[PDB]
Image (tube, coloured by chain):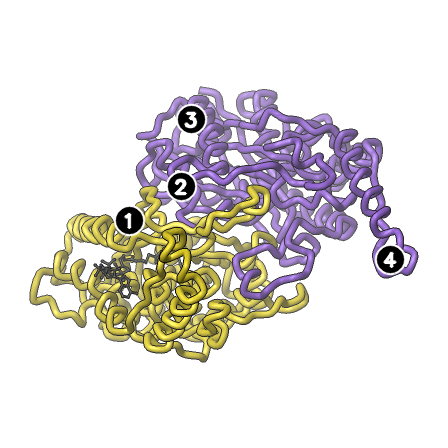
Chain colours: A purple, B yellow
Amino acid sequence: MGIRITGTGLFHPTEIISNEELADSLNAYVEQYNQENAEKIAAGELEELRGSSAEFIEKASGIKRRYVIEKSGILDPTRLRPRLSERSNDELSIQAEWGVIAAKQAMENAGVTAEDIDVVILACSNMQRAYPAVAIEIQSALGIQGYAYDMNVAASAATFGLKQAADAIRSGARRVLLVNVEITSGHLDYRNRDCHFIFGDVATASIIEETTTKTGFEILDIHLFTQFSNNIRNNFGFLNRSEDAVVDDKLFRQDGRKVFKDVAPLVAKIINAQLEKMQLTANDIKRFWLHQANANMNELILKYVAGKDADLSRAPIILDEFANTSSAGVIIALHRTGHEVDDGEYGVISSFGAGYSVGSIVVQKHVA
Amino acid sequence: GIRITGTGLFHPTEIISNEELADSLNAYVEQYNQENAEKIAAGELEELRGSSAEFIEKASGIKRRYVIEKSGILDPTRLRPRLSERSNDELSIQAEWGVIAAKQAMENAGVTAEDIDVVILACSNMQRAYPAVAIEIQSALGIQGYAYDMNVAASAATFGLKQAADAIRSGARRVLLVNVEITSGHLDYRNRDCHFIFGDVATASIIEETTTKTGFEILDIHLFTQFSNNIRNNFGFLNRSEDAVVDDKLFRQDGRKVFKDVAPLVAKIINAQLEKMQLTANDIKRFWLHQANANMNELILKYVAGKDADLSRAPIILDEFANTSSAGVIIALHRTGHEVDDGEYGVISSFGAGYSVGSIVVQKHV
Ligand SMILES: CCCCCCCC(=O)SCCNC(=O)CCNC(=O)[C@H](O)C(C)(C)COP(=O)(O)OP(=O)(O)OC[C@H]1O[C@@H](n2cnc3c(N)ncnc32)[C@H](O)[C@@H]1OP(=O)(O)O
């Protein structure tokens, strides 16, 4: 009671990569690969590589384009990763820089300042370093006093973070700043036509406070769920060096088929049980802010929740423009469309993805 | 009514002593200074200095430490454990250690997988980004509910306890909190300044809503962070895209700056916390402090509890384990918690990288 999301903030890099640009880049690296290894392809010693097309990506997912930290390196067939430069310890890290920009916007939108925040949580799928925590770096650049920590549960990091924010407020925090910084172009495999299009880069932020006097989305119910799966996995980590690792699995890897069939009914079951628990029907939900990876999966989830007459008219899509931004996607959607909910109406925020993790949150808008 | 009701501890088998560690580093430096005698006389590469086991012990109180794999750390040509990649079908090393510790803590609390709602992995370094290894631990124990990874380096256990407590206040019955610290994967064994500081370990804790189980009731928590670059490791998933070359992808610290900054800070936090609780230092039977440096702990004790305070009020396990980062306070509480009788007070207090400090006032119940 009285715990509300009172502000959100969005930052994305300026450069954009269209599906067509992405497919042309992959197709060049494929052509080049199949040439240099024409021999061992004929002997079966090496796998022939397949390409893709803008049309396949868009029908596969709904994605048309994405923002990226740096465009030329990702598209260069001889690199296929952003062109970045080490910063010194004296300057803001990349992850902390993006986080600060999104955070400042959430704070202005909530009408709060640095002295009003007690907790900073950096919740996302990959931290730029292990220590000092990037959340502490964000906290300091913003001049916030209190404490901060980094939290990783990949696709549901934002809903899990909202829960942790609610718990900390319930026990005494005044206001929590929750930050999601996803530089997915840093761990994506741009050589793989099945995953190279899925992800884009972004940072989002949220202000969560105890209040009855500020406009926001009041949290009514949270359900969090994990169930270990290896269908999404990235084995990059600090022990690779000691393992003298050689397996080529240190980037995002996935069995998209299995993920689709496992997670869609799982998410739907969680949402339906949550709605029944709250004595609401699908028809009482003004907006579903679902994970933003695959428009076809979301459409199927609403069929399981709101009948086979279902439909995305109340389930906004931002993945056409952002692609999949992992933990940040639900927050992007809420940022862009929360204004379409009226005073007193209900919405549902639901993350789902790697780990298998699922976070589902029932909110109600209040206007002060 | 929320209590820490069990703790568990796993350490690997092999022991490395100050002597072996100094000989191994001394052999590297003699060998490095041998191949580069030119550029050290021609002022291009610096002439490496060695270390002494006598220095290590008096600087910190550390004598030995457990390690995941001994031979590769001591090998002056490698200076890092010899591990092998496991396939996804196998339990990861970090999950394996956390499971072993978790079962012991579950046993000591009289609890089964059924009884647990949340699993938190809270340590200084995660083996991988996704799927969370806390989820891997959760599934290996058969626990149902949710799990997540959380990193605040040295204070990850006190921060995790706060998070466990807050989750119970919101509806969780029981939380399993795990701290797995394979520091040999990110310690710099070439660096005389820090190669002796860290050991490997895993700890676990059960936190429950209860008034009828023996354990430590959590009474007050003060968490604090303040960005400092005085402890930093720049390894990360963007190094590949930065085409990184700076030799800072391992543990680095300015230990004496850390000492001056953090020691008075910890004592100010504890004193204010005691005042808030309307306790005095005399009311605290055991201070479970971060297990990094015995001199630092000695100074913090004699500042909060006065000169003449018995040093047995601040138990030390860093002599056997070296610095274990987030797990240090949990080891100490595990090994000397029985030393606190019913109705007596304790203080758990971790501190370190990030500058993080976390401090918890507890009371024993039997
Ligand atoms: C694995 C990472 C997990 C991530 C978790 C990170 C969070 C944490 O747990 S933080 C833990 C790190 N440390 C702390 O919290 C406490 C901070 N302070 C310390 O640890 C101590 O200062 C410690 C043990 C490093 C050294 O203590 P101290 O005696 O003050 O060393 P220092 O003053 O720097 O050295 C002075 C002299 O000794 C020399 N010296 C330094 N190292 C050595 C050595 N190995 N052998 C011989 N001499 C040495 C110095 O070069 C110098 O030489 P001289 O003055 O004669 O020219």
Is label 2's Cβ within 8 Å of ligand 1?
no
Q: Circle 3 sits on which residue?
A: A107
Nearest the camera: B357 or A66? A66
Q: Which mark is residue A89?
A: 2
Q: Circle 4 sits on which residue?
A: A40
Q: Circle 1 sits on which residue?
A: B222
Label 3 sits on what residue type?
Met
Label 1 sits on what residue type?
His
Splitting the image into 4 quarters, where does residue A107 fall?
Answer: top left
Q: Which element carries disc 2, helix, strand or loop?
A: loop
Q: Which element carries disc 1, helix, strand or loop?
A: strand
Q: Is residue A14 above or below residue B236?
A: above
Residues tagged 1 and 4 counted as in contact (Cβ below 8 A): no
- Identify the image quadrant of the C terminus of chain A: top left
Q: Do badges 1 and 4 share one subunit?
A: no
Label 2 sits on what residue type?
Asn
